[PDB]
Length: 145
Length: 145
Length: 21
Length: 21
Image 1 (cartoon, rainbow over the protein chains, first blue to last red):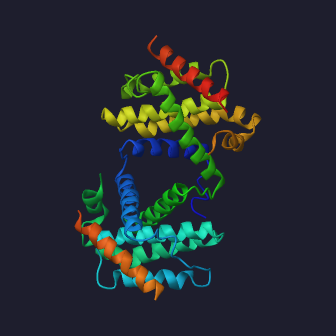
Image 2: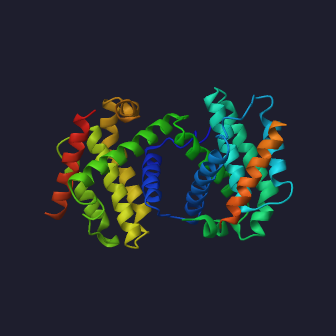
Image 3: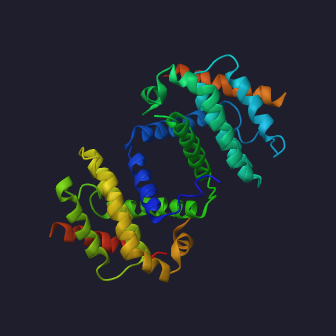
């Protein structure tokens, strides 16, 4: 599934030090600053979401046969009338909640499929907007802490 | 360069989902369990450490030209008279603190060097002991959750 | 319709998020 | 020395950690 190849002792080191740097708010690369920013926006998104509503894993009714159609319908409507960074955060948090719900219901197989669907949507339908709007560094400028 | 936008977006997806599953407690890989147990053992180690002494990051006066020799000396005395899981945890926390101290004092170059020095020491002088004592799985059983 | 409603809740939360930045 | 004291603090905190497991 996710990260099935990062099994070396060297990766254990890399992972521990990455955790410690970002835990104290430090980034070691432009990519790292994007990941930290994205993780934080998702947390803050989900806390905003679950207060106004229910937690967004609670509402989902997915199966392997319907997961894809459910994912595409929600995402198509999310961006139907335009893109912005907030909606992209919502998009990541939605994928995340699909994955969490899937593992919670013993459909772990869907995690890697959801990851692909998100990557595919990102690269074919969001990435031009991301490029015309300052790239991920601009997202870090606006949402980084 | 060709393909890097696409690749970066795939890494964001993987990173966000992984953050989100482990956030909700789900260990999906084998090394995912080890990493999670190591991150938490690091956190506990430093909480005790700073509760008894100063901050682990303040105890170190390090420069790029001098960082290697200092790191190898501290680690060699730490394991000079034996290995155990707690000292292995101390070894990760030390490296973590070195990296934090380095970024804070504007020597970001040292971070990926320290990771290499740690991985080399881990693979040459700790991995035999680890194999004799149940592997990382035994560690997860002792320090996870 | 379940998905349309979830789409609406995601879209409005994302927009409030975008506005607060 | 300077680093002898550091590794002593690391060694003793790790040993306490190891006992409590």
